[PDB]
Amino acid sequence: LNIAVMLGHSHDVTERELRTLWGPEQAAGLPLDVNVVALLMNRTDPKSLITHVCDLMSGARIHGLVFGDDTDQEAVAQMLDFISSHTFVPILGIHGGASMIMADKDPTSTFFQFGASIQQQATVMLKIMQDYDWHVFSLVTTIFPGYREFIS
Amino acid sequence: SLEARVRDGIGILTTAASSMLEKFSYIPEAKASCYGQMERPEVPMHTLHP
Amino acid sequence: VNIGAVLSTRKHEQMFREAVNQANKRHGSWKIQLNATSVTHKPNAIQMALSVCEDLISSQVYAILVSHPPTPNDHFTPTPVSYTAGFYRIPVLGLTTRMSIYSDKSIHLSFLRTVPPYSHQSSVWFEMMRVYSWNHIILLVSDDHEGRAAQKRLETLLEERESKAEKVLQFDPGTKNVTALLMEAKELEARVIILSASEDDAATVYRAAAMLNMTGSGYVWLVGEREISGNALRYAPDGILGLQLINGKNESAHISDAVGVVAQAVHELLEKENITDPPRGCVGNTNIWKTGPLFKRVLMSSKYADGVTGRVEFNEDGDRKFANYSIMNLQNRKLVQVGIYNGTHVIPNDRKIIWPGGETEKPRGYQMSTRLKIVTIHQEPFVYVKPTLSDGTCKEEFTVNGDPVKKV
């Protein structure tokens, strides 16, 4: 197959061949044969993002592009999902931008994240509290998007 | 570190592709281009999402 | 200020220009006076998003208006504009989009609409419930975001009355056979149904329920607004109570109201402390607006009633509040109005309704069953258990004086 890789040019902005050097011999046999099309990115604009993804698609029969950003705009993920809802290619983010989980994605879109939702955070919280005998508390919340779900 | 994340993503994708191949191998290609005129949804089956 | 918009057809552009000219001539902000920009709904999805920048962000607009074209897609208009303008935190103003995924202000960031989305008709359902003394419902619901949101809203509203609905049965969207759930919903003690789903599912459930004699006497239905539309009006049982929005599929009044609100808000932002300019150019700048969130905050808090839509007052998540619903009823497959909803109160008309069946009464929503199922346990002299006799009857035993012993 083929699966392009894009990076945020922040941590590993060097040795693109090293990322291209995935699985020198194999990993566990490698029944299929895949090659990366690793492309370094730049400042991410919506028109720029769409044009890059579409043109890069129009090339080497592309598949689940593994996106990764360096900044924190909280919107790129949404934009990313949008593309994955109109072009049937999987997309899963790793670092930063495409890592803050949105509540409810579209039901005909293939897009996956690597973070943890609010429910898991609340579960870890209550597992910490239960382990130090702090069985009394009173949560306070502001008017911020998603407080109803957390309280519920 | 980030390299482990990229390795994990690539591995998960090739494993999903291998599962689809071992199931009913007919692996599709790119959907032409997204810059075209009209798109007619006629996907033969759930490609690799399930 | 170069306020643009994304309308449906070319004819509305002249009306938009006339409205903006009237607003500028009446009262506004000095700045560069006012202007307008237009673009049509291209049916290429992704392309449209790009075009937005190439015609609106490229001109450094301050607010974007989006309207629903008549193509049956239900999401075609608002999503691309909302996402693209939410990247830069610039606020948009939706005109006629009642879908309830947008009243979720954590994915769309900045999105204001001038028509209440569906679930407020569940609020109206509760208000109408109060005035007729009904206390037992078996409401059905879909399984997408719409149905879950409506059910959650109704449950939240009903929780304040220290009561609860009876059953909350639900089905997958776009099914083909439903009669299992409807058969399950028969042997209960409630006679009010608050069905709320899509048009095709509504037609399917109507056809399935017509064979179970559920449309007869004493079954008060309640159908909100979308399941008495085009297709669902074919198999509807005479006696339903459908709602509507008085100023619904209309654009002129909504365009005028949106222009008035936006102009009044702009005439208030310029007289402030810190003022910034729109981020002209789609490519290049990748930072949020310095006045974006403040612009949304000031726009949301704005009371103004001088246009032909009713009182305008955005609430909490900039959704809508204080709208008008015009109740109707179906007699001989002919919709007739029988009341008006003015906001937090209902107002009956001088017209007689006909419940399903055709009696002119107020069918009680309750029943009594009187078929209680009792469960026991084999233990002690309390409840004996003995193997039955193959003849059909247990036996005939006696006591100290030969008195018969009851057996079931």
Image (cartoon, coloured by chain):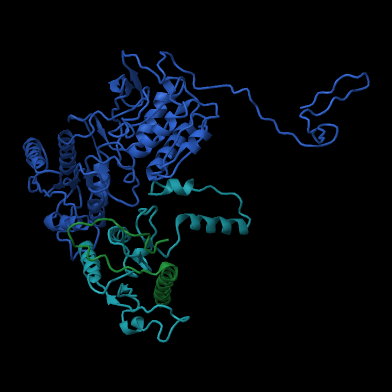
Chain colours: A cyan, B green, C blue
Residue C315 location (% of width, % of height): 32, 38
Q: Quadrant of residue C343?
A: top left
Q: Nearer the viewer, residue B27 or A140?
A: B27
> Is A32 positioned to the left or the right of A13 in the image?
right
Residue C339 location (% of width, % of height): 31, 20
Residue C348 location (% of width, % of height): 34, 17
Q: Is residue A117 above or below residue C185?
A: below
Can residue A139 be seen in this snapshot?
A: yes
Q: Is residue C341 above or below residue B35?
A: above
Q: Nearer the viewer, residue A124 or C293?
A: A124
The residue sitting at the right extreme is C400
The residue sitting at the front extreme is C391
Q: Quadrant of residue C103?
A: top left
Q: Nearer the viewer, residue A46 or A26?
A: A26
Can residue C277 be seen in this snapshot?
A: no
> At 41% from the left edge and 42% from the top edge, which residue is drawn?
C176
The residue sitting at the bottom extreme is A25
Residue C29 location (% of width, % of height): 11, 43
Numbered disc total: 0
Q: Quadrant of residue C285?
A: bottom left
